[PDB]
Amino acid sequence: SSGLYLYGIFPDPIPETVTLQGLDSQLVYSQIIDGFTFLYSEAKQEKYLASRRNLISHEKVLEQAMHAGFRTLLPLRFGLVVKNWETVVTQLLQPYKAQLRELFQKLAGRREVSVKIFWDSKAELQAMMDSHQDLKQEEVIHIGQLIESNLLSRKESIIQVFFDELKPLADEVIESDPMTEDMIYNAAFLIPWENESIFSQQVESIDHKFDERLRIRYNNFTAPYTFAQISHHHHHH
């Protein structure tokens, strides 16, 4: 009654010379089924807690596959344990072949990078009160609407420059909502694999234009989760 912890799905064979280690230090295997390669390890439990430790093990199996050449992949969300290969075939594979082939077409030769921009939220709020209009530092609804809309403008002036100036090196851009209070941009870019060096330098030359006003967090190597999504197919019962 060991199930299968699944890490990702790849279009090509992965050789056994690619040594890999996963959750609980289990060895990681590949398993080809009709031209789809599933990277997996033996699951001891049915469920794994998303502890910091386990999330790192999961993330590194896929990153290590990418470092070894297997850059096109659907990466799976942490925790995916299925009972047996029959269930992998009937539920995960058979109904999804076409979407998985399309998806491998879109990702081939491409990579996800991310850009998170932070500013000093407090400082830029007080700096904005000192601007062109300056009230005294109910109709409380009106005034809290006017600050919130003029704050958005001040963010969006920064954001827009980064978006106009990086978008030309990318095939697709997906923006997500701020995680922290200081975060003003959280964007994933899908770029040709060989655009990374120029992208990296472009990010840096844009930042130089804003002086020490921003913190930039650029991740240049990650499994492509934002751009590898599978919509639901019909399942008969």
Image: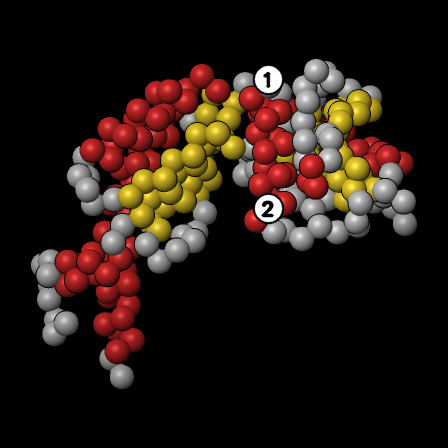
User: In the image, is 184 to the left or to the right of 18?
Assistant: left
Picture quarter containing residue 66?
top right
Element type where label 2 sits in the image = helix
Picture quarter containing residue 151?
bottom left
Answer few, some or many: residues within 10 Å of disc 1's Cα (few below 14, many 20 plus, some between 14 and 19).
few
Q: Is residue 47 above or below residue 220?
A: below
* Figure label count: 2
> Badge 2 is on which residue?
53
> Badge 1 is on which residue?
69
Q: Residue at x 33, y 44 (%)?
A: 117
Residue 56: image x %, image y %?
58, 41
Answer few, some or many: residues within 10 Å of disc 2's Cα (few below 14, many 20 plus, some between 14 and 19).
few
Residue 28: image x %, image y %?
73, 30
- Considering the image in quadrants, where does the N terminus appear? top right
Label 1 or label 2, whichever lies nearer to me, is: 2
Q: Is residue 229 above or below residue 201?
A: below
Q: Residue at x 37, y 30 (%)?
A: 167
Element type where label 1 sits in the image = loop
User: In the image, is 127 to the left or to the right of 19?
Assistant: left
Residue that lies at the very extreme toward the front in this rendered image: 25
